[PDB]
Amino acid sequence: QEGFEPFAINMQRPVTTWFSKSLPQFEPVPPEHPHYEVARMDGTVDTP
Amino acid sequence: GFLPDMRAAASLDTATFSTTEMALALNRYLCLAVLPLITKCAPLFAGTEHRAIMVDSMLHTVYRLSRGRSLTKAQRDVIEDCLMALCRYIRPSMLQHLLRRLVFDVPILNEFAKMPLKLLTNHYERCWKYYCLPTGWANFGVTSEEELHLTRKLFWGIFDSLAHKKYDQELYRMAMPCLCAIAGALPPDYVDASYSSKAEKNFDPRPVETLNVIIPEKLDSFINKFAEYTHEKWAFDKIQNNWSYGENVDEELKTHPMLRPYKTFSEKDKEIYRWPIKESLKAMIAWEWTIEKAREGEYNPQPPDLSGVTLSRELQAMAEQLAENYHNTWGRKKKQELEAKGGGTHPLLVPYDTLTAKEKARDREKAQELLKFLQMNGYAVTRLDTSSIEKRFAFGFLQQLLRWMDISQEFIAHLEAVVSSGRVEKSPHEQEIKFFAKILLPLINQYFTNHCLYFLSTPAKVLGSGGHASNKEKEMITSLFCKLAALVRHRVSLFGTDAPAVVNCLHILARSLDARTVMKSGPEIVKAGLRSFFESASEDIEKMVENLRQNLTYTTVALLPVLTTLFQHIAQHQFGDDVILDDVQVSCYRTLCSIYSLGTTKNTYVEKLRPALGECLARLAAAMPVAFLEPQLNEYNACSVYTTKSPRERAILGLPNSVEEMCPDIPVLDRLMADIGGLAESGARYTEMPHVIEITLPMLCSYLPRWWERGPEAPPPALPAGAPPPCTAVTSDHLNSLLGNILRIIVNNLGIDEATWMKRLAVFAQPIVSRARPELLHSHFIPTIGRLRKRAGKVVAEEEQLRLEAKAEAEEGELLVRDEFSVLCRDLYALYPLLIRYVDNNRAHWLTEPNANAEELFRMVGEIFIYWSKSHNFKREEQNFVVQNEINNMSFLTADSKSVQTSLIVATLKKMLPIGLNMCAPTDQDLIMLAKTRYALKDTDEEVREFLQNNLHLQGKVEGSPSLRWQMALYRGLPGREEDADDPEKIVRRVQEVSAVLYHLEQTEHP
């Protein structure tokens, strides 16, 4: 009576959802990380 | 570009260059070019933490130039405006130094102290939440307890200075805002680090002249030993930093150049380093505390002085004072240096209190190092006990206010003496009277206004600005309530101009008061005083009833609002279940009997006063826990006097051992409601019985609803408690009868224009309109609202008849129907809140199962709405009715509880709008859309009805689209829905009605 459609009404299959899984896994360096920075200097003489 | 400029100006500000032509040129240049530029750049100054020191320096030097003499008044104003505009955006984290300087320069309260306190009060209004809230103010750091300590000293100093100085109208008038701002900003439960006052006498750090007197020989060897220990702890710290004592003179060695083991360390410089410790310990012996010699006798010192830790209270306090001694000596030598320079000031020169933390840290380190060296070889000082409860700012202010109340009794006694003995205007203490009248009542009013919830809070119910008022604080503020009560009781004729402030202060004292703790194990003196005040009020009402058959300007003007407000405060904290349980309700019995007795008399005074008397009796009834209409059921109730007193004790307290004949004036509630129903059936007006609506209806409607919970209908949690006849035996049927009688008197007094009391007649109807039976709709609301719609239609017909004729007499009749519109709008505003609450209660039932009666009500109230929309004169009459009778606030209250034309659009249309759309089919929305378009084409109702009849095929079908398929499915799945509504006549009727309602709604939203 207010014109507000129920969500996922016309879904036939059940709606798939996503959960925040708590499991430590390594991920690469974000170059926009506000606190840490990684530089990549190579080719210098007498230094690997 | 700038900071050197006014620095040079301050240097030239000296007396020798006060009249210098170049100095005046510099001042003129600054005030015309630079300072206005600072004013323009003031908004840009936000977020300047990284230049905090130089911002503080510019603030201090701007203050110095503002005080700088040899300036025109216009230049003074320019500097003051620049300083205040800059301060409006400067964060206090850079401003605390200027604030402390202004705090020490304001106590003069003359010359250059008026604008300073104005800046302080502006900043305190800006940062009121910053100082009071324990949590840091949003996006700003938390205020420092040292800052609160400073504001406390500032409060007390300004207060005592204002008390001492002669009453100047300008001074008091412009100083009261600042003092109130300080009082509001400083939290009440804040406790200062030292619960004392400096009471001393660019700060002047008076040194310690103790260098003249030698340290006593009982500890002189100790003093030299500590000097050696300090010069050896230098080496200790260095060697903990991997730098052993060095015997070579050179700059590369970070230790002392001649730093050797004491066996090889020459004593020639040992005396040089010894003298400062001599002076330090002379400074501390110069005070009242002296270190004790329980020890015997007396380059790395193994025992270290852990100066960072705390210690006992008084010992750490004297250590802080010794750090203060270091500071005042250093400040005095630096002040000699400053006077040698002749210009500027030393920021470190401020008192050892309000210092920066860094030199506070240094002085604390030195003093606590000395104290720890005292401790590890047994040196404690020999020469109050104030708890934090007493250290509280609220507690201290209440102490001061007790002293000022005894002063008040003194000067009002003198005033009574001089007014009885002719007239003596000259008073050796009129300063006290003016001080009171100008600050004390406003100050206490603002303080209790901004800390009302704090004083109202309890140790169990922690809330308010602080955690809670202490129990002793609550009992003393209750004592102050009784104190001001007696203050206005006696010599009421005096301070007549101050009487509104007095009554407001007494009202807020009634507020922010926990009477439960006063009753339970509270001060018996205060309890007896408040009971005596109740008896005094009772006998004053008795004098009023005997007189009506000065107290005229005190009882009605002052008392009745005061005890009325106390009554609803007690009711809405439910104090009455305890505070009025015993020794108070008997006085309440006497007062209610006296009121019901005066109601018998029809004197003009009682007829014009009975509104407020009815309000007071309703409030006391809501605040009183014993049965007064139920004498037989009363003895079951535990709060009754009879169950707590033996017959002999009743006799000695004056109780005649029977409620029936103890209150014979007001009969049982059954007889009362029978009489109310009989009068409603007889159908007379306010003029015929003023007593009923003003007394009995407040009585009836204050007893039935709040005692329904005490009735059997409300499920008793305790079956053994409910087994005996409960204190109240009424039911929702009784409340229904009450509502019916109220609505009958309403439908009676639609006609008369003298029914101004509809305000209360609806206000009290609001609590009772809840728990309304479903049959009430068809029994009462339909006939009454139908009569209202008929009358509105007649008045609109009169308006149309007057509009169709253009004549001055036609406009005169138009004004007459304006008056008729106004009175029927008073009636409309009286009736609408009840319908609003009724539909908000029964709407879920109507939505779940549709009701034809509800739909008919919707149609006819929509008719009322459409007449409102058509008649512009009706809207302006509603406008002027609302503005003159102040019904805007009651409209807002009705909206929030359940423009000034919102009432009709929210009640007539938005309340039953779901009801309106429920009865129309989803397939009829196409007809609704086309009908609203054809209305937008400006066609009449009959013509659009013909169009709807023509458009019978324009309605859609469930098979047409899945979007409306589920709407159709739910609509047919509604249990109350049938196919009978599919008849074309019904379809076109409902579609036209709903489309017209939506048309007028969208026209109202946007013409």
Image (cartoon, coloured by chain):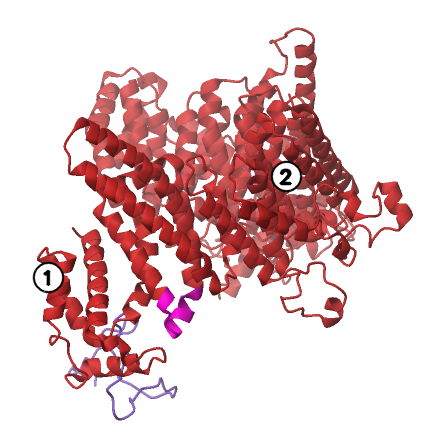
Chain colours: A purple, B red
Q: Which residue is mark 1?
A: B934
- Give how far across and how far down residue B880 sits, in percent: 32, 36
Q: Residues within 10 Å of mark 2 (few under 14, many from 20)?
A: some
CA distance for labels 2 and 1: 75 Å
Residue projecting furthest to the bottom: A13
- Mark carried by residue B165: none
Task: Please check the rendered image and state whether residue B845 is part of the magenta-colored stretch, yes or no.
Answer: yes
- Give how far across and how far down residue B724 sits, in percent: 77, 66
Relative to B354, say whether B416 is above or below: above
Lower sequence index among marks 2 and 1: 2
Helix, strand or loop under label 2: helix
Where, quadrant-wise, is the N terminus of chain B in this rendering? top left
Q: Judge whether residue B311 can be spotted in this image.
A: yes
Residues drawn in magenta: B842-853
Q: Which residue is mark 2?
A: B396
Relative to B740, say whether B107 is above or below: above
Chain ID at mark 1:
B
